Amino acid sequence: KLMFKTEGPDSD
Amino acid sequence: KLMFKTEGPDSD
Amino acid sequence: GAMGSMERASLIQKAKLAEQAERYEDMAAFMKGAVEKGEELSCEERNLLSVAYKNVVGGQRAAWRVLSSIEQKSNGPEVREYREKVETELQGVCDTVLGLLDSHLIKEAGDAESRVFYLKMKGDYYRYLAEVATDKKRIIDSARSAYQEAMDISKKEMPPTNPIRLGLALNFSVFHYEIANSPEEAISLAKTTFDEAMADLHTLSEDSYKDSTLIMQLLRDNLTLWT
Amino acid sequence: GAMGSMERASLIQKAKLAEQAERYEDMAAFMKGAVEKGEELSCEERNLLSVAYKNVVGGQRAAWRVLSSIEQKSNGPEVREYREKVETELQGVCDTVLGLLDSHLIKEAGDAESRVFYLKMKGDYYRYLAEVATDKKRIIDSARSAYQEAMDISKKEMPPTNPIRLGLALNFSVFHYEIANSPEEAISLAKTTFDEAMADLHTLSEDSYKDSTLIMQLLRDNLTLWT
Ligand SMILES: N=C(N)c1cc(-c2ccccc2)c(CCCN)s1
Ligand SMILES: N=C(N)c1cc(-c2ccccc2)c(CCCN)s1
Ligand SMILES: [Ca+2]
Ligand SMILES: [Ca+2]
Image 1 (cartoon, helix red, strand yellow):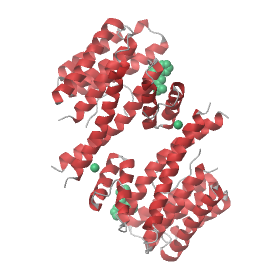
Image 2 (image 1 turned 60 degrees about the vertical axis):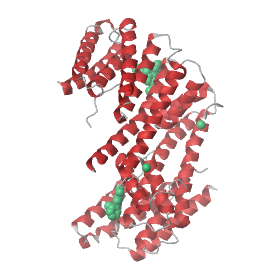
Image 3 (image 1 turned 180 degrees about the vertical axis):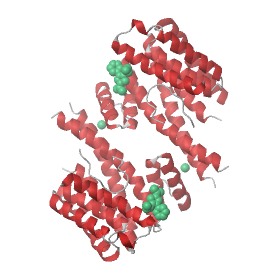
């Protein structure tokens, strides 16, 4: 999936 | 520490 | 529970060690123990709790999407069974964090910086449940409600460059875009949030400017993809 | 134990899913369950078991070195206490893998490719115990003995380009260099291993050539650092 920008660590 | 090359995934 | 015999300050110290060791499970368990001491969290302590669970739930979300994509491609029980196993552990982490927020972080959060932080987390981890949810409507409405309450307080109480406010609006716009299937709401929230922050940057120190522009750039990255 | 009611083939399938999801704890638990079915492992199954535990023990070794370095810098109990916590879980994973090798993978391994693989693992995870060991002499002698038995069989039974043989000698040289404090033995083993593989490459397919030169390059990277 294209994951959008959300706050804090992109740990996924 | 300088970790030397050992076989398989350097997962450390 | 597990951390009931360790000192509050030792749990916080050990959560900081865990972060440096990238032991995010340990970091989450220590911060859970810290919360269960029943005292309010400082700003640094709120950040430790959030970073810890975000790193844990991140691993599970990455894992879930890999498995869900294999499952969909394959449409034996093993793929469905293991996807469920991961989904169930993901739901357990979300349920644990929501448990901490309801018992009793939110009801004792009076200041805007703490209350908006906790309601954002509440929207966030209902959104993580939403991602894997096939009852889905209620979960989605729980996220919206937490987000909206956070947004109302942030607009009244915080300047438009407030990084917590900026992070809230970033996440709520992504909620709008891919959970509520309201991409137009997403785009509107991201533009208005960006432009309002831009017009307040003149008020900030160098340090604060860095902080706010980093989150503004995340709103721009999303807008670039969405338009 | 935990995996006693799942089918052998389902554990193997689920270990492969876990690897793709980067769920290395799950991958190790499934491969442990696969081993405890009591049937010998295929070459692919040995690789799954090794990759799984290597990824798990890797996280713990990285974690341990970060904590040990803070501990040393700081020379309250928290740093020592958390370093111990991580060290104890690291020892538990090493003890679990050694348990599988002794009960009963090694005694049922008759072929060179399987027996050398298992003795290498035995030397490897005694070396991981050696890293955190302050009795240390016996652990170190356990690693040497496993490595040496592996080396004797590999020299007699496998060509010098055999990737398992090459990986064994890579690891045993690192054992020599930083566990036995015999850097001269390390350098000699790495040079002789490299040069003997070089003179046998002419015998290999394109596919096998790739396989052997990748491990040879690891011997060269170490020799570059050591000389
Ligand atoms: N341990 C961590 N990763 C974090 C610690 C803190 C913090 C440190 C001092 C005072 C308040 C908050 C974060 C706030 C984020 C703002 N830049 S994040
Ligand atoms: N699942 C994994 N990461 C691995 C699978 C296999 C394998 C696949 C077919 C037959 C034998 C072994 C590995 C061998 C390594 C040689 N290049 S590694
Ligand atoms: Ca399963
Ligand atoms: Ca501890």
